[PDB]
Image (cartoon, helix red, strand yellow):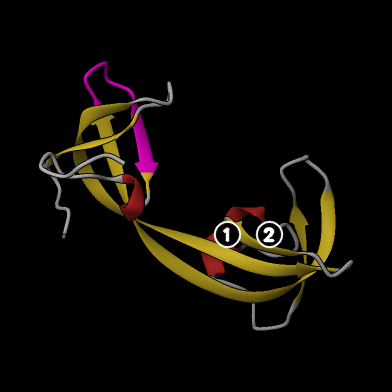
Amino acid sequence: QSITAGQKVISKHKNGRFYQCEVVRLTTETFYEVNFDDGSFSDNLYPEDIVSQDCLQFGPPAEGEVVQVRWTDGQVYGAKFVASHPIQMYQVEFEDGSQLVVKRDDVYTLDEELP
């Protein structure tokens, strides 16, 4: 059930197909959740996407605090900080040398059926 570093596993390569790969490191990804001024919700912002303050250096903003965020479209939107949640993830390396940082549910042991 538990996946550890150095373990050979099976996961989807960037080309979309499953291949054996090796977990080279267990990382911790911190995602920010915010409510945009129009009411829409985002649950996967990175600390760096907050452009109204420097979260990478001083931590997440306070609950409900007003912030500006740089969205995936390169634009800046006003919003309110909701919460922060660190997620344990897996950095995997395939035979060709490419790597990906994936979630637990995207990793499989050699003995289990796919998908």
In the image, which disc is placed on residue 10? none
Query: In the picture provided, is 44 more to the left or to the right than 107?
Result: right
Q: CA distance from mark 2 to mark 1?
A: 6 Å
Highlighted magenta segment, given as a residue range: 94-101
> Residue lying farthest top?
96
Relative height, residue 16 to residue 88 (above, below): above
Relative height, residue 56 to residue 74 (above, below): below
Picture coordinates of residue 53, whole percent (x, y): 69, 65
> Residue lying farthest right?
38
Say which residue appears at 73% left-offset and 79% top-offset: 65
Q: How many marks?
A: 2
Q: Quadrant of the C terminus?
A: top left
Say which residue appears at 14% left-offset and 52% top-offset: 4
Instruction: Pick whichever, 35 or 9, lies toward us.
Output: 9
Query: In the picture provided, is 104 more to the left or to the right than 56?
Result: left
Say which residue appears at 21% left-offset and 19% top-offset: 95
Instruction: Pick whichever, 42 or 65, lies toward us.
Output: 42
Residue at numbered disc 1: 47
Residue at numbered disc 2: 50
Q: Quadrant of the N terminus?
A: bottom left
Identify which amino acid the numbered label 2 is placed on: Ile
